[PDB]
Amino acid sequence: GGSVRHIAIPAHRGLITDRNGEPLAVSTPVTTLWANPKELMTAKERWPQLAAALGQDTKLFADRIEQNAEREFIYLVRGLTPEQGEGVIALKVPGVYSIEEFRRFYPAGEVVAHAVGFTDVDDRGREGIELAFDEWLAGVPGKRQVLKDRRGRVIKDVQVTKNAKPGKTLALSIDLRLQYLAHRELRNALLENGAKAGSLVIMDVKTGEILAMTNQPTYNPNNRRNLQPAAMRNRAMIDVFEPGSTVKPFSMSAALASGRWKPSDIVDVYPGTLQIGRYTIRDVSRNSRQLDLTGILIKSSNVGISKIAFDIGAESIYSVMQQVGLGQDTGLGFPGERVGNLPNHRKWPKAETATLAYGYGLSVTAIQLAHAYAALANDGKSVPLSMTRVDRVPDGVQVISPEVASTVQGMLQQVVEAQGGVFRAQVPGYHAAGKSGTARKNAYRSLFAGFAPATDPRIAMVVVIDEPSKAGYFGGLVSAPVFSKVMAGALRLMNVPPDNLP
């Protein structure tokens, strides 16, 4: 006949949009039904009709209400359409009450699942942006009072103690139009090459924004039914791998900055192997003798970059790699994010000096690799990463001098356009620049990292194809065609003028 209890007032979770306001995560009003078993015990002849309205077996529902006859609150069904909730309410079953709360709906579904993430049944972020910015998005629940009978019947409201503060809107750096394109093209490439998984990262080299981030396999954050953890793996931020030949441009940046090397310099790589003690440096193709610095990148000559590294010292190469973020914390604060490993030595031996120079030993993520190529594309200035829209561009750090960065840009354009280069990475109408690579896990990862336009870069991109099972596993056969198709759409959607038209 009288008992006051504080009930919480759910807060409206903040809207998540892409960089242009397209809805990505929307709080949707839902109707949750709860029951007071004490009042249900006075209306047993109504249980089968209530059981059928809840899609529950007649006897099982009766067993559930009986075992909880002493309690005052149980959940009947959580998160219904307001239409569905009022249908059960219209039955006038004594002891059945409704609660108005919110549930997330993700209009893009599987296309941006890993980046956006999801909430749980209690509207708490548990993955992706939903967890990374949960305090910003959640708001503060409110406090209300209600009078409860000694039999549990709701009698009347007493007062509101504190009003709910709704969550705040968040606009991601993602361009949903680019996301749809990268999601589709990465999926097509996986089917064409029969690959298990893949990752694609797009960045604005001037602002540090992540314009697109897609992983295969993916999942619908709206269905939530037996989602195996394989499809929920945010591979672009969690998978680490040896970058291989894709970090040779940074060994080259340290070479061109040492004062001892120029692009015209030649290196003798005959006969394709180089013995360092018991360790044998081996090139994939061993049909060369003298190569200039660009030919070293075109052929992916581990021997050539090793001899350059011996001359300039590993410390200069480590410094460039550390400053562009390889093996470093990205500061993005995503769950399960991995940093990788950029090893450091007090005294760099010859073997570790070489394997560092051509991308063995150290382990990076696709996000780190894209961030490094963005710095190279941004005339050597590294801008911090961001998964939210950047209105005020932060000051970068000039890690590679603009002259050296401009020289490596030209050499990477030749890697894509010169004879024997990665011509399948060429973007029609534009000058693209990039570098192919392979990461062994038999099983390999096909890598391509690049940027465009080569003469005035705007967009950096990394493609990781995990274990192709059809054509050759080489980067340039599998990953380069994806770069070409996705970069072409990224340049068009951002109205970047073509720099390669007759």
Image (cartoon, rainbow, N blue to C red):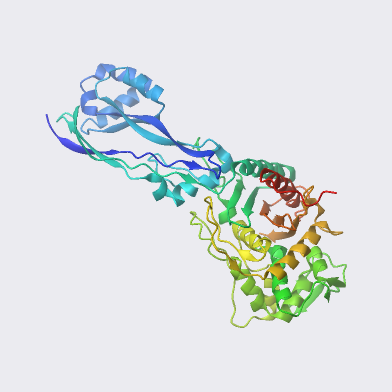
Q: Residue furthest bottom?
A: 347
Position of residue 474 relative to residue 139, above or below, is: below
Give whichever of 221, 181 is nearer the camera: 181
Position of residue 250 relative to residue 444, above or below, is: below
Give whichever of 55, 439 is nearer the camera: 439
In the image, residue 123 lies at what x, y percent?
39, 41
Give whichever of 124, 42 is nearer the camera: 124
x 18%, y 31%: residue: 148
**Quadrant of the rendered structure where residue 241 is?**
bottom right
For the N terminus, the image quarter is top left
Across the whole image, how many numbered discs are drawn on residues?
0
In the image, residue 384 lies at what x, y percent?
55, 61
**Quadrant of the rendered structure where residue 393 is?**
bottom right
Position of residue 325 relative to residue 450, above or below, is: below
x 59%, y 79%: residue: 345
The answer to whether residue 206 is seen in the rendering is: yes
Q: Residue furthest left?
A: 1
x 65%, y 66%: residue: 380
Position of residue 233 relative to residue 454, above or below, is: above
The answer to whether residue 194 is seen in the rendering is: no
In the image, residue 354 lies at what x, y percent?
71, 75
Give whichever of 322, 262 is nearer the camera: 262
Horizontally, is 35 left or right of 501 in the view? Answer: left
In the image, residue 101 lies at what x, y percent?
36, 34
Horizontally, is 63 left or right of 234 in the view? Answer: left
